[PDB]
Image 1 (cartoon, rainbow, N blue to C red):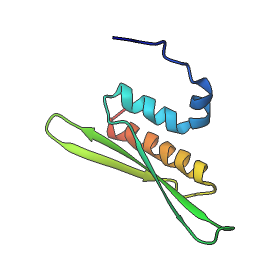
Image 2: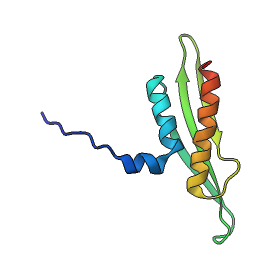
Image 3: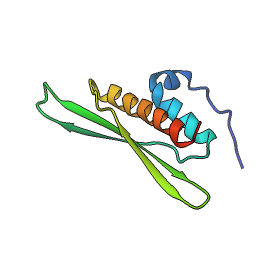
Image 4: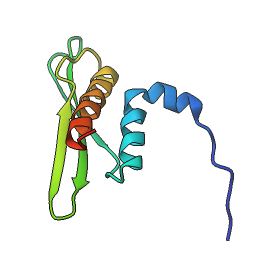
Length: 97
């Protein structure tokens, strides 16, 4: 077998920002890691992006899926972070925390 020390990847965390906060939240609460996708439309000089994130959750006898997106888009990256921020808010309520 083999193993290696896991890197801090501090830079990646800081760049990810809200995206990593959502990941961390989901991990601790035993929720499915967040999945991201993008929709783009409009002129190349005026491209409008929508970032969307999905978080899947299970209960003792129920299942549910949370979907959020960065409605107030400015940039591709920003939209994804906004979607994560929305998910963070929703998940707080969903988990009754």
